Each structure stands twice: as C-alpha cells, then as structure tokens.
Length: 432
Ligand SMILES: [Ca+2]
Ligand SMILES: [Mg+2]
Ligand code: NA
Image (cartoon, rainbow, N blue to C red; front, side, top):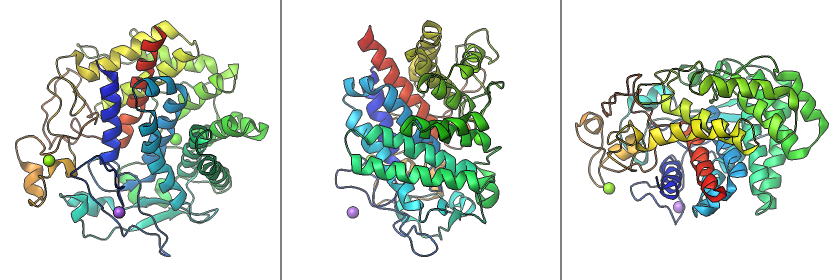
C-alpha cells in the first residue's frame, strides 16, 4: 500500500470537514465558505473548526480528542509524515482546529463546546454552504461545568504547543497558555460536559471525566515538566484498571502510555501491556473471519485503528514492539484493502462509494442538493478522499449504502488514530 497517498488523502478528509471561511489554497473544490455566522452569545467569533461527521455540528469533545490524537501521532511519527511529504500539511490540518479552540475559549472560565443543534442539523440534508437554520452555540462555565471537555481541549492545546513550538513559537505559546487556563478551569469546576450542554448527550455523551483530568495533566506535564501536573496525573489516573478501548470517551490507555513513554513512569506499563495483549490475536477482542479486530458494531474500524495507533506508539518505545507492529499493520492493512476492498473512500480497490456524508453526497454547484441526494442509489457525486468508514459487520459484510448510518458513517475521530498509525507504518519503512 502507498502510505504516502493514504496520508495525503486522510488529511484531505479533514480539509473536506472544514467549517468557516476557507483559505485561498483550499484543495476541496466542492467546499466553500459556510457557517460564517457561528458565534457566541455575546457575538464572539466562533467560525472555523471541523464538522464532526457527515453532519454540520461542531462537537467540541470529539473534535478536541481527534486533535490530541493527531498531534500525538505528529510528535511520535514526524519522520513518517516527512517522508510522505505530508508533515507541513498535517500541521496545517490541526492548526485549523487549534485556532478554533482558541476562539471558543472566550474567557478564562468559559469555553464554547458546541455550535449547531444536532436535532435541527440532522433533519437537514444538503450542503453546509446552503444551511439557513439557526445554529445555537453552547458553552461550559462555572455554572455549567465540563471537566472532560475542558481537559481534553487542554490536552489538545498542550499537544499542539509541543507540535508547533519549533516552527511557530508565538502560536505554540498561545496554545500552552490557554491549555493551562482551561485545565485549571476543568479541575476547579467539576462535571460532565454533556450534562451541561445537554444537546450533546444524544451523540457524544461522556461517561466520566476523571480520565480526561489525568490525560490533560499528562499532556501538560509533557509540555511543562512541572511536578504539579505529574501529581495530578497520579491523582486522577489508574494503575489498576485496563482500558477497554482508546477513543473519544476513554483516555485511560492514552495517559497510561503517555506517562510510561514520555514521562518515564513505570507504574502504568502493566496496564499498557494488558491493553495491547487484549487486542492482539488470542486476546479479548473478537476478530472477524478475515482478520479485523471487531470491538462493537459502532465504528469497528475506528476502534481497531485507535488500538493500532496505541500499539505503534508502544512499539516506538520498545513496548512489545514486534507483536505491536504486526497487530497494528494487520489492522491498518485490513482497512486499506486486505479483505478485498478498501474501507478508505477514494483510495485503493473498490473503496466505499456512499459515505454517510452530506457535502460529498451533493452534486456540483449549481445543482440542487436535498434529501433526494440522501436517497439516491448511486455513488456520492464527490469523492470524499481519505475518509475511513465505520466498517463491516462482525462477518466482514458491508453493503455500502448511504442510509447505513452505522457502517457507512465517517467522522473526525474515525480518522484520528488511523492517520497516525499510517504515519507510523511509513516511518517503519524508513527504519527497515
Ligand atoms: Ca472520559
Ligand atoms: Mg464534483
Ligand atoms: Na474568504
């Protein structure tokens, strides 16, 4: 597989998800300016960010987690991004959401965590450029806490500081200052963001915020080396529980691995190894007949690519390296085409033609786009290069239907671990 092309197209997927005022060098010809009215309740500019999935909601929790995970992969697998000619484009990719998080952090203890009503948004089928419905914006604050959302965004900002500090120190320093402030807000104003922003509860409900507090602390310790953050990581982290998955809701193995590798903390390594062995063949995750580690019907590709990412970070730091590399390669290669078809839109052999995705489902301007384009039985008019679809059922079956909102789903978080894993595999090619 051409990993250079996979990386190029994965970053193009994120570019096709951009909201707001698009740059002159926009590479997605069917996308234009959209949601230019996104704003806070006092008129604060909230334009930009990524649309979460095939919809036009800006869901701050997965948007931040996808950014943290992408930044981590850029830090660890820079050599693979560079070899692919995609390093500057990867930085541009996450600069987009990091700038959005800065806008959303309107004051020390207020942070906008959603733009768009998901009920209204999902009732619409059409271009983002054609939207006319109200797009409310909701924030977390001392009266409306969201320790999970705030600490995940702090994690993304601290990871961003580390990514950008050697090329754009003014940007990186601004990210770190806001990371510190947002993390203090998360620690001192405690609650579940999807209870305070209740519209999010039907879509990205957070089950617990303690793992985000440990994750944000671990990232701030990597960024600042200040003992108080390492203390916070032990305070809210677990050395006794093994993560079920790595994803936008569960940060456990993320901070365990981060503290083991970047911070040299040996107490967490047994739980990292437990996670890896649970996902490896012979573990606790069932594999489809054709070899996909299949955790659940909702975004199995996302869960497996996330585990592949964790495994490849582990291998880089010589944690079960041979087994981690073989497991990770097997999972990414399933998604690239090993079972007979690619699961990455616009890539490889017979890629998915009907991603559940509004803008790519619309024909070129000036043609009409509405629910006819949801229902139409053929391929999406635009190729959504790089999007990793949710994936097959537990028997490797995939119908490739736009109405299959489970298997044909695409989303920011689906590609986040995937993209870093591909960069890691590219880097291993340089090593060998
Ligand atoms: Ca959590
Ligand atoms: Mg076209
Ligand atoms: Na413009």
